Image (cartoon, rainbow, N blue to C red):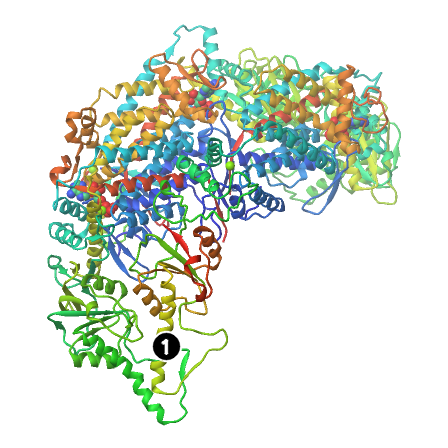
Amino acid sequence: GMNKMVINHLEKLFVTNDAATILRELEVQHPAAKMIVMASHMQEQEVGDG
Amino acid sequence: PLSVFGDRSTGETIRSQNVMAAASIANIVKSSLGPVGLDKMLVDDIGDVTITNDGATILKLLEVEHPAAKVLCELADLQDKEVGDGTTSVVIIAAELLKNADELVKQKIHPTSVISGYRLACKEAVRYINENLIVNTDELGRDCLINAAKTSMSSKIIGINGDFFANMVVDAVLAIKYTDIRGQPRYPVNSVNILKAHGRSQMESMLISGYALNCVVGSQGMPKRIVNAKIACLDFSLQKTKMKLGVQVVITDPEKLDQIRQRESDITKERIQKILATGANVILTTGGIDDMCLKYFVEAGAMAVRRVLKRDLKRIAKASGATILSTLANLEGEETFEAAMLGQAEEVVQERICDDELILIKNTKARTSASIILRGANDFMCDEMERSLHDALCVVKRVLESKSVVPGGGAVEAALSIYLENYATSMGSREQLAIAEFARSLLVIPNTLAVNAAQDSTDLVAKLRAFHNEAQVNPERKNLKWIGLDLSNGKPRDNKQAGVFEPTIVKVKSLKFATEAAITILRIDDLIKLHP
Amino acid sequence: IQDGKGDVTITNDGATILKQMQVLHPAARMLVELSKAQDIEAGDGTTSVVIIAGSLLDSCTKLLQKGIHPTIISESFQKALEKGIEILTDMSRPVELSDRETLLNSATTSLNSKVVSQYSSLLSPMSVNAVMKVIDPATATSVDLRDIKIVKKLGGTIDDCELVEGLVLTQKVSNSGITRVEKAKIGLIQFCLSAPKTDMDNQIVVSDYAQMDRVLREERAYILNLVKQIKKTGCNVLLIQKSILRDALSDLALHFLNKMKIMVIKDIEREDIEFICKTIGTKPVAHIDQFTADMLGSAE
Amino acid sequence: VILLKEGTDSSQGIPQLVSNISACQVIAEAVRTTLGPRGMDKLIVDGRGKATISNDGATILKLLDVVHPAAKTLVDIAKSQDAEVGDGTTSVTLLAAEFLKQVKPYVEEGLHPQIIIRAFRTATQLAVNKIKEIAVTVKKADKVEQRKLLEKCAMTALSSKLISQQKAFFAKMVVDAVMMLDDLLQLKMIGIKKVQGGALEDSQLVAGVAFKKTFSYAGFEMQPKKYHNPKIALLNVELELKAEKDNAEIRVHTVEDYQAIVDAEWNILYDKLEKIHHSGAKVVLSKLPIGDVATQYFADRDMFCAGRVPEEDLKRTMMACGGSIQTSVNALSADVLGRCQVFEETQIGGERYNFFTGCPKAKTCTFILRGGAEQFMEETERSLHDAIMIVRRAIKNDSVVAGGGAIEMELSKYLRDYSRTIPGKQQLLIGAYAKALEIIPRQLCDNAGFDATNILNKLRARHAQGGTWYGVDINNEDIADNFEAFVWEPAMVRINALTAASEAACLIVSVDETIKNPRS
Amino acid sequence: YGRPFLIIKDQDRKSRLMGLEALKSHIMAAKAVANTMRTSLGPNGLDKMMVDKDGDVTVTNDGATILSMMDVDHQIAKLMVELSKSQDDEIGDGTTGVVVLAGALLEEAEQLLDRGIHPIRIADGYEQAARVAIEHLDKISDSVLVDIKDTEPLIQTAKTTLGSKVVNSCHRQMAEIAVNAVLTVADMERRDVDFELIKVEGKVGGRLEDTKLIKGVIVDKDFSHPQMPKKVEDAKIAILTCPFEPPKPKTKHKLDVTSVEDYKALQKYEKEKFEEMIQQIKETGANLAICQWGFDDEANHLLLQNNLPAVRWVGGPEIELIAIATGGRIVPRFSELTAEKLGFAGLVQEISFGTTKDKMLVIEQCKNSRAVTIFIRGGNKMIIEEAKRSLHDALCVIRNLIRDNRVVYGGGAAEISCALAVSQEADKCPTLEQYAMRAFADALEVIPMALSENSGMNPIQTMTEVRARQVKEMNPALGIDCLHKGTNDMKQQHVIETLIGKKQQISLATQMVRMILKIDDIRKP
Ligand SMILES: Nc1ncnc2c1ncn2[C@@H]1O[C@H](COP(=O)(O)OP(=O)(O)O)[C@@H](O)[C@H]1O
Ligand SMILES: Nc1ncnc2c1ncn2[C@@H]1O[C@H](COP(=O)(O)OP(=O)(O)O)[C@@H](O)[C@H]1O
Ligand SMILES: Nc1ncnc2c1ncn2[C@@H]1O[C@H](COP(=O)(O)OP(=O)(O)O)[C@@H](O)[C@H]1O
Ligand SMILES: [Mg+2]
Ligand SMILES: [Mg+2]
Ligand SMILES: [Mg+2]
Ligand SMILES: [Mg+2]
Ligand SMILES: [Mg+2]
């Protein structure tokens, strides 16, 4: 998996391929996508992978 | 310092800017190269959308401001005019070798040396192409034409049905043979009229023997089919005779008035009977025809076609043997018409198309002619087939004019590069570097080909497209020099086996034009942009 | 150089570079005038003269800083130029014509600093042949470049440049039936092959029905008479001067010319008549009565 | 409704990576002309109007306002190389940009970034191993040769700076400033004080401690400015009239008690001053301010006072004289007051400077460097910091390697030879790595106005079989044995440059897509 | 690719100059600065009239001051200003000379690099020529005697320095007062001169001839309670810090007066505190009291009726100077004022300065006073300021001569001799580097050219003739006859420049021009 670079709303560079990190530091406005974001973050909190 | 009131860019800045502009144009045109290249969509400001693949049309439709890219656009247009096929190839080659030359210059190599190196390299590449990479299309006939047309169509929209289209192409080109110097055949393409219809599928495109005029019968009264066509081509309109600007009538006694009014029509009448006296039943004219003359034609039984263009009427006159007439006047002082200057055609019928009707002229007596009607799904599809068919016609014309073809699929460029590296081994001056770089630039087209088919280029060009090493160092292994990349498995295959050939004109002209355009754009040392 | 409008040029001649570049300083304008004057007088060195002038002005700035009156510097520069002209004259060697080798050397040297340098082997011999085929190399004392017509057309490559001892036209043949002529008899025309019309006000009045037939027949007969007089002299290709206020070619006239198997070239500029006459040896006619084969140009 | 917030800009695929590579070369072009003895200088004007003049990669890249993430990576690599070894900031940026430029041809077609990243990792591991196994160590532990090694390393460091013509004058100088440091090599133990006026060769190294005249009151200029064997009373207490506790309230109801308390404040101040005087110290120093009353008290008894001294200068005085700072005054013993050979207040370029010189056991130093402009002395200080950092790093191990592009050419030859046994595509990538590592001598020749191609070909021919250590001799316009020409560099700078450049190249290549948010 | 990428924040407005064009711009700005500073050089030079943003005007010839007030924006001009200020700091004289030398050197550098020579090579040549020039300058110098017994060489040097400034209207007493002030203040054993002991004070009115050197202290105060005598004879002085007010602890305090008896006790305490204060001032025997922090009405009247004149509100530095002059000690409390802690005053007098209400005190010492004071009088504020900066230049020259003792014979002779040495060395030097040496020679030799041009003579011919005279007869003290007295020999004309001043000029200009040549790229918003 290739690393991805994200510029947050405060102009901070995040280069990484960790799905939870790029998903958190990337603003999402759709409701269903927010649902999937919540599910993935809960998975990260419960286990740490997946 | 200087008082110029403008902008000045000097040194490495303008060189890098020119290289970037050339690379931008090359990157726009690059994705539409090869049989696996997918064509582009160009939509205007107002919504006039077109779908095209050829580089010339893409570059002409694009709006370019940087002159270093305008040079490449004009190069593509020139390659389109002089040859017709290989328009993307010339732009890609020119931009790539310009980039390589700039890379050389960045290491403080004088641009005069690299220009001389490219110029000599182009001479030697043309010599190598003309000497060791041409096969005569004389022992191979009626099949090299089909293969060349098919490989020209492969990248186009009509490539899927190439085996059906290529055929009519050569047939069209075989119906255009002409003699100029009494012993040298010529093939005047642009004399095959191409018509666009947007009805049924591609498989039912029509190849019409004889012309296919895009006009309609003047009035519904006259018949729309003539069993034996006596065509009377005219460059002379038929309306009531307004006298002239200089001449104006003046009536003193009233009685003399009405008479001249009858004359004001009768003159026209008379000419019509003369045209109808020689058994003529088809009337073609560039000028308009008013209602009374149409009435004469319907009463007699002949059809009249008005507002026919000049080029199609000239083609019809040449094909049917008719003599176009600006006026009805002999070497004496009396108007007359002769039956010896009437064209004869086997049929003339107004045939209906998707919604409209067009006139077909079938089996003209004098010389065989041809026309093509392309059926497509919509107007965009039809015009794209028209452009592809024009490209194929040009390719077949080039092949027949010069009976010599070279392998396609990047075979010639790989062979040129691998020979030119060893050529530039000699001439141990700094100049040799330039020549060597030229060789590497010749690799830009094969690699991108493998790029466009979801394959890896340099993963295979190292050895798979290096069979030319043995084809060069070993004269007994020459049969491998006709090898090019194949995208069914991404392997070096003998192009002679698959039949991928292109006329040597495309390669020679593309190389010469690309290297000269690069030389012209590379002499730039600085730019002065004057304020408007 | 790209001017205000989107037109560009790739220039190495100093005169062109300085002219296209719209300078604003008076010294710069005087320098560009100097460059164009040097081009007019010689034609080469239009960069070196500007470089010399600017360089020795930069030399004299420190002379001004050293407390020297400008008049002394000017007079001393005049004396230095006087000595330098003699130095250059002594340094030279005599050159005499018919020595093609030194002429080719000079042409190649002139072309070395240009983009066409690599073509100089196929472009300098014709460059000197152009001059040697215009002026007599015995008693000349000057040559003219006006009678060296440089015609440029887009397409091809540089290696396709050509030198022709004949005449080149960018005009187009009106009758698209005849393309080549062997043993051509060229004749310039300065009058008009159309319906007659006097210089002062022209008017025709028709009062009867036969008059329309009469005027049509008479105009056709007049045009046919003119074309017959043109043809009976053996003229096989015709050159019509570009005429305004009267149609140079009528469709009926062109039809008759085509009928008698002739080639017609129309719309020829007035200023080109001298060039054509000096090239193909023809003499212009402004009246049909003086159209004779005794003064009709000929070509192979 | 759209998935992301409006104004989000995303770039994916090959063109994004190629644009990142091009941005890397563009940002590395800004410091390219600042290598080698013929290196040039960069002037950067801030938004406030202040202009900084320097020719080190780290400072120039920091001063440049960078917003491209790949150019940001180049800035970070330069800054980290500065923070690790101090010298070699331009080399890391140029090496990273040259790696990326050499590989971009291969990335133009469909080359998977993982394979080229692996090629970089293998090539850089082999390169670091070769550098470790080629650098020569004298392994003699003798003072004369150690001094020569440090002097030559410092001299090579001072080249390509503003202090080039005075290399030998400054180089050995900074060596002394590292000789007289303890076995911790703290960078705060050698101070740098900049003063306007004077020539570049008027700079000096105070083996004790020198600092600018802090302040004075009505009573100064009366105590003598020259003591020949004084005792320094380092203090941390203010000696002036003040409130006892900043919240102490005095509550009395008789005038006798009022007068007693006034006399009591005066008495406590005088008793504190009497303790200081009876300690035997002659010159006193204090972080906290010294009032006018104490100034007059010490003037009346031939004692020098100096208040509001900086913390760093007071600690340097501690490390020079050998005393200890006492916040309390009740315990001025005899083993806590530092002593120095000579104390003297002198005039330097329109300022007054106090000097404590002649300390026998000194673990600190002070640099009085002169100049004509503030940027002149600032650039001199930057060069001196570069030199002291390189000597500080080299003092841990005296393993050296020839500079002037010799080591880069040696690694290039080694990698070229190695990339013939390895079959497949990795051979081409390792060859690209070696051709990229070939950049430093070319850029040195370009800055020196040489024929870069000719000198590179001569280096390659003479260095394939004719012997290592051969770099570019700028003065002779040719190639020369740079180890025998005493152009020495510690191997750690090249090791760190190579590993950092590899890491940055891998990080830049390993990106396939970038996203920019609307930066709310 | 088609997409243009952005790397630098706000990069659409930033400007960049690179390559040789940037160096041309640098050299051009330096040439402009040097041309501005050229006219005001030498005795025949003309002043410059600088007006600041507040609109206040000052007419001055000091190059460092002129460039400091030059509100300039070019970075090279800022570097030139810093050059001039640093030369003023280290030496105090020759502030225009460094600017002119740097401009000439950069102009020669431009001429050289037009011929495609590396700027670093030019800098190396400049450094070598500077070394040669400094060695020759040290070889050519001779020494004067820094002693009170034979002070005349000091007057000669100060008079040469005071030339080209308005104070040359007097030109003899200014040098005398400068030499006397520096000699008195200087600590000869340490060879150090302290400028805080020379309170250069000015006041409008009078004439420039009235500028005197008080071997004491002048202060801008007046006797409080004007009923007291306006002057006292040789008097014992009591320099004091604490005010004549009832004391109070620094710590915040509350004094609760809880009864009428407490109120009476507080009243008596205050009254007796004043009385005891005055009594213990008088008991020491001092005639004059001086207080830093001022005092109140009761102290005034008690001081008056006890025949003890006093002044108040004397500043800190003024208190220190008074105590140094009188030989007394500053005491911060009345209870520790002994007889030994008084100072001596030859006489303390009050002066009124004409019709204005302003008053001043003069304290004249009959004993050794380590401090002095230069008092300046004139008809304009501009004259006063120019006079005091010119006298500061003279004092700086005198102290430089104290700390170095060696002189060279200026007026252009030093520059011409150094130029000949540089050219002679450059003769026997391998090529590719002698061009920089000869450029350095010409650049340093422009100074006589500018001197002669300012003097009105033809520069080139006069300079060539004096150089020929210097090379024919080995007399390296031949300079431009700027004052038109004949005698190209500059020994007889008595022109003296300090060796450290000239060598600092050369070294500092060489280093600044090296930095300027080093710069390649400029990035500015
Ligand atoms: N069937 C095929 N097999 C291998 N190569 C092919 C085949 N058809 C076309 N090519 C190659 O792909 C390229 C396509 O060029 P193309 O883009 O059609 O020319 P143009 O630029 O005129 O449109 C040609 O250079 C040709 O060599
Ligand atoms: N005397 C010299 N001769 C040749 N090359 C040198 C010399 N001194 C330094 N170099 C080269 O200069 C490079 C470093 O340049 P410099 O600007 O001094 O430091 P940085 O590495 O921070 O840019 C080194 O690679 C070294 O090889
Ligand atoms: N009487 C004099 N005759 C000739 N030259 C003089 C004379 N007085 C001063 N000069 C020269 O004038 C130059 C400039 O002196 P001045 O303008 O007074 O101060 P600064 O040196 O600060 O410019 C000095 O270098 C000195 O040699
Ligand atoms: Mg994971
Ligand atoms: Mg094609
Ligand atoms: Mg020329
Ligand atoms: Mg360094
Ligand atoms: Mg002076």
Quadrant hosting residue E85: top right
Compare residues E305 and D203 and report the one nearer the observer.
Answer: D203
The residue under the point 17% across, 39% down is B136
In the picture, the quarter occupied by the N terminus of chain D is: bottom left
Which chain is mark 1 on?
Answer: C
Badge 1 amino acid: Glu
Of the four image quadrants, the one with ligand 2 is: top left
Disc 1 element: helix
The image shows residue B205, relative to residue C93, as above or below, that is below
Q: Name the residue tied to disc 1.
A: C218
Residue E329 visible in the picture: no
Residue C142, quarter of picture: top right
**How would you rate the neighbour count of disc 1 (Cα within 10 Å): few for under 14, some for 14-19, many for 20 or more?**
some
Give the image location of residue A1, x and y in percent: 22, 37
Q: Judge by depth and name the residue closer to the eye, E173 or B210.
A: B210
Q: Is residue E418 left or right of residue D166?
A: right
**Depth check, front residue: D288 or C97:** C97
Horizontal arrangement in the rendering, residue D387 relative to residue B326 (left or right): right
In the figure, C254 relative to E367: above or below?
below
Residue E139 position within the rendered picture, expressed as x and y whole percent measured from the top left: 71, 14
Q: How many marks?
A: 1
Seen from the viewer's position, the closer of residues D312 and D60 is D60
